[PDB]
Amino acid sequence: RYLMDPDTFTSNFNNDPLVLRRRQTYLCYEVERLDQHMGFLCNESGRHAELRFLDLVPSLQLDPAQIYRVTWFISWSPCFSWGCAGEVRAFLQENTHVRLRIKAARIYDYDPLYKEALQMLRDAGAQVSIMTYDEFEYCWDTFVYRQGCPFQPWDGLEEHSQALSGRLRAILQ
Amino acid sequence: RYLMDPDTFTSNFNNDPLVLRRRQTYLCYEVERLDDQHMGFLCNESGRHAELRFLDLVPSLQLDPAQIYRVTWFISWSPCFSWGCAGEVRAFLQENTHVRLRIKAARIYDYDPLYKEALQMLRDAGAQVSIMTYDEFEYCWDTFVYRQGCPFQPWDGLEEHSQALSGRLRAILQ
Ligand SMILES: [Zn+2]
Ligand SMILES: [Zn+2]
Figure 1 (cartoon, each protein chain N blue to C red):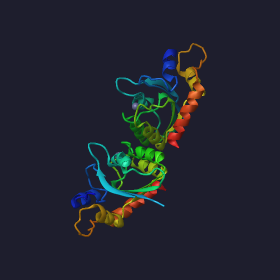
Figure 2: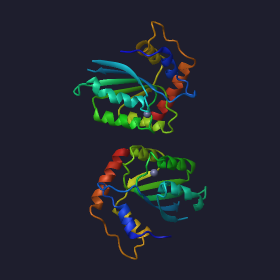
Figure 3: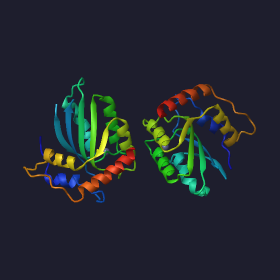
Figure 4: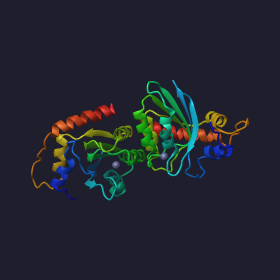
């Protein structure tokens, strides 16, 4: 599996919510059978990382008779107004042997309907939560070309995660 | 104030759910204080759904923030999810805790794939959502329509459609 540049990880997964950022998304994924496929994806030429993950599901050749858990570690929560939540809902309805967990570093409130995205994905069976220190370091250790160097947290990581988690839990309550 | 044309009422509040319709909405409203009345109707205009146009006019009603008000919507379609109506109504009710909102819908907005999420979100926000029955159609005819003394005439299957839709709604909200 090809490993991500460390600078790319840190700049995209920093969870300080008061920074204006570009609308790029990185999506680290793992699939577990209940196979083990793993990798990462970004938005490319108008196609959001979430839909690019859906595009490659056929190449994973999942057994329809087997149950799989798909985990996304994603730098932004999925949008509504550009079709991501809708395509992801359709995929879950069409592939009931798949259970999806979405762990988001930040909430994508640049979309006016971002709350509708989170709420509808929850209703479709996705488990949506905000990334914590544990997940950030796991991603550093798993998807990043770190050359044996340990994860070094950015300032306020824990406070930002708890603040965003409280906001997400209020949206979904 | 101003009364609706009868053909406009009949074509917009017909409750046959299997009819291909234009995505226009009519919303007849009543506002009363509980222990001061406003009434009117609204449709979608230039893309803005009637529900949001009602929220737009709340300031001009000059409601006392200290008093409780019951707002009743007789609305031809239940409010949508995918274009933001349910979310905007939830925000308004959270910001205006002295409003008690009752939504009586002629039809369920099946054109929205996420219509069930809208209904559940409105219930969770404190709105009482129900399906219009013969009683409500006739009340609206008697109240909001330029009927010139003519009685309400039901369309085919009115009662059957209302009970079927009511059963769907109650199952969604159980
Ligand atoms: Zn998207
Ligand atoms: Zn709407």
